[PDB]
Image (cartoon, rainbow, N blue to C red; front, side, top):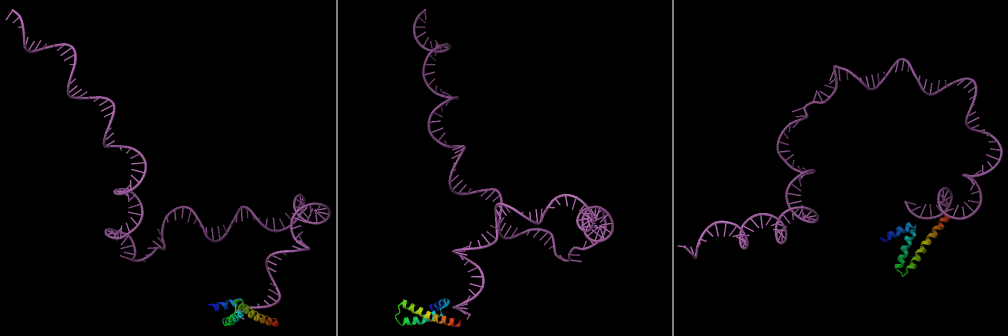
Length: 62
DNA sequence: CCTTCTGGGGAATTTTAAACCGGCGATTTTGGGGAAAAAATAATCGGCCTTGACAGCTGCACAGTAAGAGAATTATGCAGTGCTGCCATAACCATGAGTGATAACACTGCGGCCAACT
């Protein structure tokens, strides 16, 4: 199906965040009118928020 | 007594039969090509007719000559040792040439560090 392959690719790119955020943003856009560009913008926003949180945690760990 | 008729023979001419040679029309024969059929030769198939073997197994004996295996004996080639002489090599200095090295930039290999998944 589509969801399983999406999650596969997301994890292969090291983006379980992508699997999680795509669910939320997809639900929101299906419940709203989000142009594909804005949907992608929200996707990248969530990805980089989680990525920056992880990077800060790793730096503090070091 | 005389006249007319007839017959034989030699020469000239005509016709028909026979034989040869040539010309003309027909069949035959030779050559080549294509197709069909027959026969010859080789290979493959089935089957009948006839008989050998299976019945403990073959190792040994003698004949003569030659080969070979083992042991003893002998010959010879290698090695070992001493003394003397000759040839090679090695040691030094000089000069030339080749290669290992050094500087600089570019590309690649290896080790340290960071992150992602189980």
